[PDB]
Amino acid sequence: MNIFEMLRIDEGLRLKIYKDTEGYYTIGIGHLLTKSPSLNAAKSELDKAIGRNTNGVITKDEAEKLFNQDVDAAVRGILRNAKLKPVYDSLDAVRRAALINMVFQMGETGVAGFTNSLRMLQQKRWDEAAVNLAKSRWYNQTPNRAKRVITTFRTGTWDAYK
């Protein structure tokens, strides 16, 4: 297991524009296109992202390309963020993947706001961090995915993904 396989499990793969769990136009492996209710706007973003006129459909290779860019972006977002970087640096590689997963789903600014959870993770108070992480809109709206990510933080194992 690794961050790519983990997020593939959590995000799936769809080659046509779909709406994500928040109702936002998305494609591939959880690649958010726009929060606009306009499908045409989403199609424009998609064509820009891929570099051709797609008409809302991409190939698996193209989906995996966006995915690699998006994982890369999540990591660089963490490293450039003054709140997230020290937490990330303090973690083992498995728990680092859990943090990347959160940033992929909610964005750097969103995760950086989990101030008390981040402190508990930095303190390596794993059970406490897990309890705090679940007191969130995140957990309530996507509980099965949040449970997997939280288990990964609690245990430092890949148990929730096998």
Image (cartoon, grey):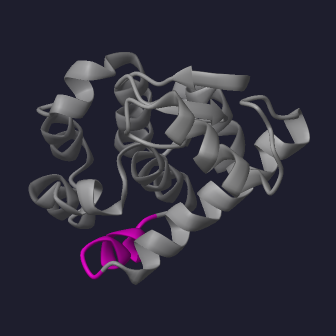
Query: Vertically, is 122 above or below 101?
Result: below
- Residue lying furthest front: 40
Q: Could you say which quadrant of the image residue 38 lies in?
A: top left
Q: Is residue 83 in the magenta section?
A: yes
Say if residue 13 shows up in the picture: no
Query: Vertically, is 99 above or below 86?
Result: above
* Residue 53 or residue 57, whichever sits in front: 53
Q: How many marks?
A: 0
Query: Vertically, is 11 above or below 2?
Result: above
Estimate the x, y position of residue 106 in percent, counting from the top left.
35, 46
* Residue 44 or residue 143, whichever sits in front: 44
- In the rendered image, the quadrant that contains the N terminus is top right
Estimate the x, y position of residue 155 in percent, counting from the top left.
42, 40
- In the rendered image, the quadrant that contains the C terminus is top right
**Residue in the picture at 90% in, 42% down:** 61
Q: Which residues are magenta?
A: 82-91
Q: Is residue 97 in the magenta section?
A: no
**Residue in the picture at 16% in, 34% down:** 131
- Tell whether 35 sits left or right of 32: left
- Tell whether 81 sits left or right of 92: left
**Residue in the picture at 33% in, 22% down:** 142
Estimate the x, y position of residue 32 in percent, counting from the top left.
52, 42
